[PDB]
Amino acid sequence: STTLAIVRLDPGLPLPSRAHDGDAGVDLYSAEDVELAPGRRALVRTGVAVAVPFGMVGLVHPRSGLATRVGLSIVNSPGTIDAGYRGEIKVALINLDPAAPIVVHRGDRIAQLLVQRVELVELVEVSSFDE
Amino acid sequence: MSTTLAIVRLDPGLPLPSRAHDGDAGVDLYSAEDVELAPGRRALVRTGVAVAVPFGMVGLVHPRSGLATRVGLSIVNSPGTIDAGYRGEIKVALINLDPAAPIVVHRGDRIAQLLVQRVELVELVEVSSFDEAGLASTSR
Amino acid sequence: STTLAIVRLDPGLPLPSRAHDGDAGVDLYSAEDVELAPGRRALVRTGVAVAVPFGMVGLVHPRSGLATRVGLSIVNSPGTIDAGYRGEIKVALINLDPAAPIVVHRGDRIAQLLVQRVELVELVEVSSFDEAGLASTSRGDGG
Ligand SMILES: O=c1ccn([C@H]2C[C@H](O)[C@@H](COP(=O)(O)NP(=O)(O)OP(=O)(O)O)O2)c(=O)[nH]1
Ligand SMILES: O=c1ccn([C@H]2C[C@H](O)[C@@H](COP(=O)(O)NP(=O)(O)OP(=O)(O)O)O2)c(=O)[nH]1
Ligand SMILES: O=c1ccn([C@H]2C[C@H](O)[C@@H](COP(=O)(O)NP(=O)(O)OP(=O)(O)O)O2)c(=O)[nH]1
Ligand SMILES: [Mg+2]
Ligand SMILES: [Mg+2]
Ligand SMILES: [Mg+2]
Image (cartoon, rainbow over all chains, first blue to last red; front, side):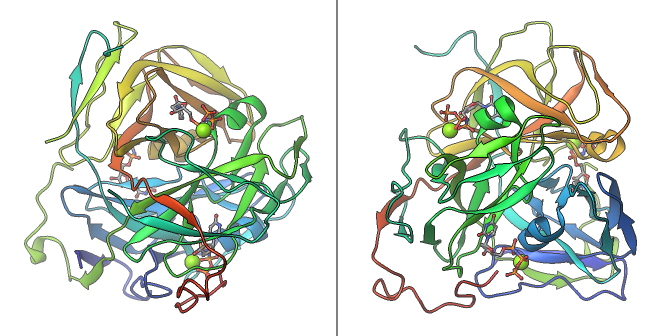
């Protein structure tokens, strides 16, 4: 078990948690009410900040059910949460349905957060690859 | 020098997903159905397979690059997350992001790729603030 | 400890770099100027080729700033760069804003590249999840 320090910037939301055992991610809540008309986007506060360990990355993924049912997606998916980042996690939701709005209420689960190792590669410039 | 991934062909008529080259990150998933997507429209497509992602790992459903450029095919929830506990059929939320040309998916077409990666099953520890936790000062 | 070999196919762009220590991605440059009208897409050259090590994968992710501010996205995100690939990295940009075109100039940072280990799992066909001792889990076929 890797530990992850989290601050509830919004104390009124539940702490993100694993929907089932072995699940890859924890769901993030919206701190806000917002309505997305077809094709529109918004940057939604989640009410949390995290300290992803050095050598790791946090990844913000859309939820499948809302994706199919209403066309909810994320413009920068997967969103990359860097180890050094100590601000509020924000989710760039977009409505990809052509005709119907998406209604987001505060306290809805709008995205999921995974933590993974990342290779912090040193780039080494070469003149050519070995053919 | 990795593990196996157990896979069921719920639809025995499709080929088993396979890793085309030894280093390729993903195995391609096929469509079990015919579906036509008009511009801007989406569908939830069955792949005909179920997998058993190992505990401590995750399955990741990513788009194929060719179809993305050639016709604007995308996946609404990309990257799709396949959890270790899930034993249902993998489904792909396809969308046509081209403004004008319909995309026709045929049964047997490759529509996505499935990667498997380790994931950290984190224990969240609530802190009152970062300065007060002893871990503020960063690069950002 | 891991290095990534990289060739600047376009010698007039900087080598990609990490914006801050610990950051997961290096930012990729556009080699070209492109204007994307609402809903249109382009395949944009970055001027670099890389050699992802066997056992790893390169992943091309959108940058959050441009995504939120102008609706810039990547059609096949996350773009998968395989260990066997030695061609130029190309980015399938798309303008998801309904009204405003996006202008990209040569030298702009239009995406970021992560490298991660990948599990090169050996697929084994089984008859069913019950017969493989695998039908006992937290979800079943729910989700
Ligand atoms: O964002 C990307 C993604 C891929 N690529 C390159 C790297 C990679 O290994 C290669 C193939 O990726 P896909 O499998 O996603 N495309 P597709 O399955 O259509 O073609 P192929 O038959 O080559 O696998 O294209 C990029 O340059 N940028
Ligand atoms: O979905 C996201 C993605 C990023 N972020 C925060 C966390 C991260 O470390 C940071 C930067 O992400 P990007 O590198 O994708 N954005 P960009 O390159 O535009 O800005 P920067 O100069 O900060 O890296 O923004 C979010 O809150 N939500
Ligand atoms: O692209 C996908 C994504 C997920 N899935 C399956 C696998 C996964 O374990 C499951 C749940 O995924 P999400 O957590 O993204 N969906 P949601 O949060 O809507 O449903 P649930 O309440 O079950 O978690 O659905 C697919 O078949 N295809
Ligand atoms: Mg879920
Ligand atoms: Mg491929
Ligand atoms: Mg950045």
